């Protein structure tokens, strides 16, 4: 045991109702909206292939010139109520919103900088409009916050002098102020998801990360805080020097997911994954033909994968400069929505089932020990292999949509062949099992 003052706080998984809710939600959407939406990946006639929200970096644009985009910020098609309806129709139980990205432009009228929605032609408090609209639909709201801030010159990448230390100490107070502001202006917030905490300046200031966590939990009862915020005394991030998880949930699976056979360790803690529709674009990019774009079933597969291993999944959207969503994103949300409406009993409020992974797809476990087989790969054998843990038998199988009974044949001790449905469902589908222990 190494002694640590700013290491892990939590024991195991939080089991208060607020965390249970965060967990049971399972499916979320991510919104990346900021000034980067205006150029849409293009600067000075040149289209850059990197992530559009990092365009300031790719095109080497100075802060003053970048933040001048505020003068064109006028999303006349924006309508918080439509956005919330879209999220509702997709089947998302929560939404995570970029309050401020690396660029430093704030979607709420912060008192602590001039780079906010207030100083734009649009003027209005976008974030407040969204919080109300989503909450009205019964959708929880979570706040993305970039610690790294390219708009504030007291920011430092590292601490190489007392001068740097002085500047950065001012920067951390500025940050605390924005955070307190967010927590008190918008007290229904359920989570803060920190990003841009990877620089050596932050790694050297673990105490501040632990402080930010404590500060926000005092202000917002039951609020959740991601692991990404946190560094310990030694600069170890996410998990501390004694290997204990910091924050309330693990938050490293970004555009990738744990292996279903090798990474079972993740079922021991809460966690949340996020993903993009193209290969790597979070903010709006005008040309999606530049990388592979996932199909709905590919996205659905990742959602169920996450849940099968006891984690949440958040699918990202990068709204247009005008405040509307591109056609591809509307189609995606609608498709995910249709499927969740039919099969979401195997997703919402479900968890790791403790069964050995099989090739046809994923198991999930319901709140009353339902075991759901979510089938993505249809075997030509017409038989779906189910190997049970010790002491578990399978008493019945049922097609979720129709209620029809599905033949279960015992092949060996602890193994069965569950038949495919008489009629091929033509899409990833669910069979529900009734199981019994000894
Ligand atoms: C890097 C990086 C950032 N982290 C992802 C969640 C996006 O915000 C991306 O731009």
Image (spheres, grey):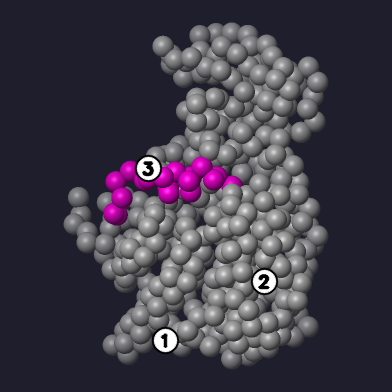
Q: Quadrant of residue 29?
A: bottom right
Residue at (55% x, 8% y) in the render = 412
Q: Is residue 347 left or right of residue 277?
A: left
The reply to whether residue 167 is in sight is yes
Where does the image place residue 183, in percent across and percent down from the top left? 43, 68
The secondary element bearing badge 2 is classed as helix
N-terminal-most mark, 2 or 3: 3
Residue at (39% x, 54% y) in the render = 222
Indicate the quadrant containing the C terminus: top left, top right, bottom left or bottom right: top left
Q: Quadrant of residue 371?
A: top right
- Which mark is drawn over residue 382? none
Where does the image place residue 260, in percent across and percent down from the top left? 53, 36
203 in relation to 223, above or below: below
Residue 97 shown in magenta: no
User: How far apart are the alpha carbons under marks 2 and 3?
Assistant: 38 Å
Q: Is residue 145 left or right of residue 299?
A: left
The secondary element bearing badge 1 is classed as loop
Q: Which dot, 2 or 3, sits closer to the camera?
A: 3
The reply to whether residue 47 is in sight is no
- Which mark is drawn over residue 52? 2
Question: Which residue carries the number 1 mark?
Answer: 154
Q: Which residues are magenta?
A: 8-28
Where does the image place residue 428, in percent across and percent down from the top left? 72, 33
Question: Which residue carries the number 3 mark?
Answer: 15
Which is nearer the eye, 129 or 2?
129
Which is nearer the eye, 421 or 162?
421
């Amino acid at each position: 045991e190494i002694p640590l003052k700013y290491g892990a706080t939590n024991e195991g998984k939080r089991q208060d109702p607020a965390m249970q809710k965060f967990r049971d939600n399972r499916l979320g959407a991510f919104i990346h909206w900021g000034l980067y939406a205006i150029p849409g990946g293009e600067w000075n006639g040149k289209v850059y292939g990197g992530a559009a929200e990092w365009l300031k970096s790719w095109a080497k644009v100075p802060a003053d010139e970048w933040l001048k985009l505020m003068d064109q910020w006028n999303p006349t098609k924006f309508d918080a109520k439509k956005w919330a309806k879209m999220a509702k129709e997709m089947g998302t139980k929560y939404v995570k919103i970029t309050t401020k990205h690396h660029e430093g432009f704030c979607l709420w009228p912060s008192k602590y900088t001039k780079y906010t929605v207030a100083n734009t032609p649009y003027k209005r408090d976008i974030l407040g409009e969204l919080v109300k609209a989503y909450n009205d639909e019964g959708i929880d709201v979570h706040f993305y916050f970039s610690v790294m801030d390219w708009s504030n010159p007291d920011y430092r990448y590292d601490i190489k002098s007392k001068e740097d230390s002085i500047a950065f100490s001012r920067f951390l107070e500025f940050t605390d102020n924005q955070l307190k502001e967010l927590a008190t202006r918008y007290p229904t917030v359920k989570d803060f998801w920190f990003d841009g905490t990877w620089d050596a300046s932050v790694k050297k200031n673990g105490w501040w990360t632990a402080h930010a966590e404590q500060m926000l939990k005092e202000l917002v009862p039951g609020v959740a805080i991601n692991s990404r915020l946190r560094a310990d005394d030694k600069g170890k991030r996410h998990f501390d020097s004694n290997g204990r998880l910091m924050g309330d949930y693990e938050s490293g699976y970004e555009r990738r997911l744990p292996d279903p056979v090798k990474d079972l360790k993740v079922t021991q803690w809460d966690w949340e994954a996020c993903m993009t529709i193209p290969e790597n674009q979070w903010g709006y990019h005008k040309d999606w033909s530049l990388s592979y774009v996932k199909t709905p079933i590919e996205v659905i597969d990742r959602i169920v994968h996450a849940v099968s291993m006891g984690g949440n999944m958040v699918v990202n959207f990068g709204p247009q400069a005008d405040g509307d969503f591109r056609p591809e994103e509307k189609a995606m949300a609608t498709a995910i929505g249709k499927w969740m409406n039919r099969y979401g009993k195997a997703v919402y409020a479900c968890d790791y089932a403790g069964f050995e992974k099989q090739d046809w797809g994923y198991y999930t476990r319901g709140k009353n020990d339902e075991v759901y087989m979510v089938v993505f790969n249809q075997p030509y054998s017409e038989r779906l292999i189910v190997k049970t843990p010790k002491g578990i038998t399978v008493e019945k199988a049922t097609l979720l949509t129709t209620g029809e009974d599905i033949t279960v044949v015992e092949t060996t001790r602890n193994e069965y062949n569950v038949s495919v449905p008489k009629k091929n469902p033509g899409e990833p589908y669910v069979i529900q099992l009734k199981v019994r222990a000894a």
